[PDB]
Structures are given as structure tokens and as C-alpha cells.
Length: 308
Length: 307
Ligand SMILES: NC(=O)c1ccc[n+]([C@@H]2O[C@H](COP(=O)([O-])OP(=O)(O)OC[C@H]3O[C@@H](n4cnc5c(N)ncnc54)[C@H](O)[C@@H]3O)[C@@H](O)[C@H]2O)c1
Ligand SMILES: NC(=O)c1ccc[n+]([C@@H]2O[C@H](COP(=O)([O-])OP(=O)(O)OC[C@H]3O[C@@H](n4cnc5c(N)ncnc54)[C@H](O)[C@@H]3O)[C@@H](O)[C@H]2O)c1
Image 1 (spheres, rainbow over the protein chains, first blue to last red):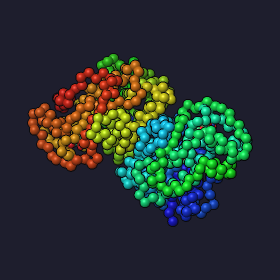
Image 2: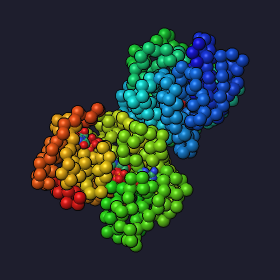
Image 3: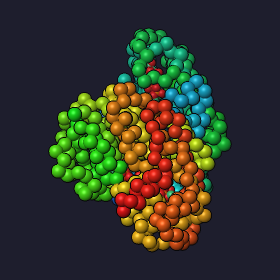
């Protein structure tokens, strides 16, 4: 049976991927420093799961972690963009050095396939208000966004120089159960859903006309598995957005209706780094992956709410 | 008034150090002497202070920027091939040094930093075209990716912390003190050293390849202007002349300068080699005072006479 190394596997997206891989019969090895990930996210009783608690930028740890692994999904990163603005030096270790050290360890070990969580943040403000195609000029505005893009560039280098097979996925806005709502910079759906469940007010920054391309985590997991099992994945990046349009006001009304409870909306100012419109051009995604029928926003919110 | 020059002991840096001291600045050099040479510097000049260490060393940078009014950040492992062989080590020199410098400058309240980026950030894009600054990026090596990431971090510190970066993408610089000892040394330093020594040269390909060569003294004038301009633009500026020199042109000009015909061994074209590389230097012409740059023959003659 094949073993998948999942860096960041104890986190939001990672733990769902772990469940899905194990269910398909893979062995899984999680490498996670539990900075935001949680052991309670993992099915620790599954005989197919191994857990290594440590830093994904640690070369000695990666040399151990890759031994006996057949492929990698590289999800470890400090996901809070704001955290990278606060401390560029520390987050650069997690957001880029981990990628570089993983490439070195995979090349030594002879492992080719790595699926990488890049981000729509690499586009910055370019193409705003239009479906963003993958060849849109990049404009990373924070250390996080620059490290995700630099990670792409190094993965492509190891592909050409050393025969790595990277599957570069630029996530748009992923949501669903286990997304941690504890920070003011947690994903807005995790925050809004937590308040609605508790019956407490939410805070809307700006006028609510901002749009995002929301993706339910279960649909992202399908793509991640397919990137692991593809016979010859494309070299260049693929957006993971649906090409959908959801305003924050759309989201407020959908969530309120799902909770069946009234929802107080207090106001805050638009946050300084807030992009107003964000939507993916889904054409490469639809060409390269089988999305089937994705979850609509309502279906995804419902599953999230019904889990809390 | 004092200028920090990281990499000041190297080829471009030491020429800059000469120019800045000649203009009355005090000059502090930070260099690990990996490829820089103390013999490149005017030791014994009362205005020159040399620090030897790693430009990625946080504690050392903190001392180094203290009392400085501006910075020229030239320290890097210039060999693209060295970054291919050792991405981990060269990333410290080619990117981490930039990030640490940003942090040290912010803490000390120093705004102006002139940065040596590279035409390598374009990859093969714009082959056969005047390369404008918005030409799509495609860094092919760790070195090129680190130069581009350096640019992005410099822009973030500008917006978030009031830094004033002057981002310059160098095309093919040449001149005295350019090390010809490596096979991946610049073709002009190699061809000239072999011409002076009367030894054969090796031409990879047909010699129709073209490059936008820039004499080091003209680059130095731009570096100094970047320090002294009152309100520099935020985005990158290509440093090239928009010139077109073939390798066969270069061989002919060296044969005319040396007075003896060069024996030309034929090698196969290098894998991935860009055939035609030319800057669109409109932004340079607009933002800087270029005067009359040295022609290739002028630069070659000045180089050859120095060997
Ligand atoms: N959720 C989104 O909308 C979104 C959008 C774009 C990109 N991403 C990327 O997707 C990946 C997963 O993000 P997530 O939403 O599940 O958030 P998350 O915080 O739940 O997952 C991050 C995980 O990585 C781990 N981690 C962090 N630094 C580490 C280190 N140095 N060593 C080892 N483990 C480390 C954390 O403990 C956590 O388990 C990340 O790379 C993130 O940047 C997510
Ligand atoms: N045509 C060109 O020469 C060219 C083209 C594009 C970019 N550049 C850039 O211009 C700058 C100068 O290059 P150069 O041609 O003068 O080469 P160089 O090797 O002569 O100068 C580089 C200097 O940096 C120093 N250095 C290297 N790593 C260091 C570290 N970790 N800490 C401190 N000092 C360190 C070296 O000792 C040397 O003195 C570099 O940033 C290079 O990447 C040059």
C-alpha cells in the first residue's frame, strides 16, 4: 500500500485530505508543528496514520519523514496573511523554506509527485473584477504571497532540473468544518458561522458588496486526491476557484437563513488590505480535473453549520 | 555622510566604492570575500571602512547600518550556476540577505536602498524583443527567483514601512575587475583575457547571439544617481542600453583591439541559452541622466588596456 506524506496534515484542509486518503486505502504520514493544526482533527486510531510533530522546514525531520513515502501533499504554511506582515522573517521559514527543504528531501529520496497549496494571493490586485486566469501578471503584496509564488518558482526549477512532478494549485477562498475561527483574520465564513451558531452579532467590514470565489473543502479534497493520482499533471499552475460570485451580503443572508435565527450585523471599516472583487477563471481547472457537481454555497454552509 | 555597500569588495561594488569616495562620501563595505577581493578596494583611504561577514547575519547588519544614510545592496552569489548546484546555501545570500537588510534598515530608520536585480527574472520571455519591465517573469533558477522575491519584499517594505527601494535589473555588465576565472564568467571577461594572453577562445554556437552590454562605469553613475535622486520611482528599471552586439561583433572588435586574430574553437550552443537579449530602457532614459554611455569598443579598449 502506498504512503502519502501530508505536511500540514493536522490543519483545516489537511485533516480532511487525511480522512479521504485513509478511506481510499492509502497509508498517510502527517508532518505538522501543531501551530494551528490539531491532533483532534486527525483519526488517530486509524492504523494507516502516522503522526510526526515538528517543523516542516527542518531538514533532518524531512529526511526521516520522506523515507518510505510515495508522494507528498505540501500544505504546511502559516495561513494567516496578516501573520506574515507582522513577522516576515519567521513566516518565511514556514512559507518558503519548508518548500525548498521539501524539494531537497524529495529529490534525494527519489520521490517525484508533490501537490502544492499555492494561493490566489499571488495575483494581488491584478485582474480584479474579472475572472483571473493563471497567466495574469503576478503582484504578491505580502511576504506570504511572495513566498507562495517563490515556492512555485522553486518547484518548477526542481521539475526541470531534477524531475520533480509538482501539481501547483492556487486556492481561492476555501471554507468548511474545522476551519479555525479563533482569529479576527480567520476566514469570514468560519467567523460568521461561529457567531450565528452562538447567536452573537457579526461584524461586516465595508459595504458587503465585496465578492469571493468560495470553495467547499470537500471539493478541494477531490482535486488534491486527483493531483496525487494524475498520470502526467500539467507543469503550470491551476486555479482552484469555481468562478462563482458571492457577495458578503449574499453570504450573510444565506447563513442567517440556514441558522434559522436572527443575525445582528455590526459595522467596521473596510480593512486596509481588502481586495473588493476576487473570482477565478475556472477553465484550466475544468480541463485538468473532474469536479463533478461541486457544492453550492448554500450546500456548503449547511454542512458547516450542521457540524457547528 | 556615509553609504553602506554590501558586496562592495566585488566587481561592480568596488567601482562604486571608488566613485562614492571620490565624491566625498564615507563608505562602509560589508562583504564576505567569497568572490570580492580586498585588492579591489582602496585600502588606506580614510573614508573607507571594511566589515567582513555574511550579509545575511542579523547581528552584523544591525552594526553595519548604524550611522549610515543610505544603502546599495550588491551582495549576492552572482553565479547562476552556483545557485543551481546549491539552492539552499545561495538562497541565504541571494534572498535572506535582502530580507535581513530590510529589517535592519527599518529598525534604524534608513529609507534609501539601491538594489541589484537582474534580467534573469524574465527567463526566456522576450527573447527577440526589447524587454520592457512588465515583460512576464519567468525566473528559471534559484538565483533568478531570489532576485525577483527580493524585489517583492522590497516593495512590501516600501508600502508597509516607508522604505525607498531603487530596483535596477542589470543586463550584461562588463569591465575591469570582472573575474574571468570561471567558465561561467561573463563572455567579455573571458574573451578579453584570452585575447590579451593570445590563447584560443571557444564560441558556443554560431556567434549570432546578441547581448545588451553595459560598461561598468556607466552602471556606477546610475547607482550613484539612485542614491541621490529626491523621489525615485517605486517599480523596477532595466539597466541596459538597448544595444545589440553579436558575439561575432565582439570577437571582431577584440581582434582589432589586440591586433592579433583570435583562434575560435567551435562549441555547441549552451542549453537554454537566450539568442537575442536587449533591454527596452525607456524607463532608464526617463528616470536617470544617461549622458553618452560608453560604446562597446570604448568599454572593450578600457578593459583590455587594464589587463
Ligand atoms: N484556506 C484557504 O482559503 C487557503 C487559501 C489559499 C491557500 N491556502 C493554503 O492551504 C494550506 C492549508 O491551509 P489551511 O486553510 O488548512 O490552514 P491551517 O492553518 O489549518 O493549515 C496549516 C497547517 O500547517 C501547519 N504548519 C504551519 N507551519 C508549519 C511548520 N513550520 N511545520 C509544520 N507544520 C506547519 C499548521 O499546524 C496547520 O496544521 C496552507 O499552505 C495555506 O497557506 C489556504
Ligand atoms: N552582469 C553582471 O555582472 C550582473 C548581472 C545581473 C546582476 N548582477 C548583480 O550585481 C551584483 C554585483 O555582482 P558582481 O558582478 O559585482 O559580482 P561579484 O561576485 O564580483 O560581487 C558580488 C559581491 O558580493 C559578495 N558576497 C556574496 N555573498 C555574500 C554574502 N552572503 N555576504 C556578503 N557579501 C557577499 C561577494 O564577495 C562579492 O564581493 C550582484 O547582486 C549580482 O547578482 C550582476
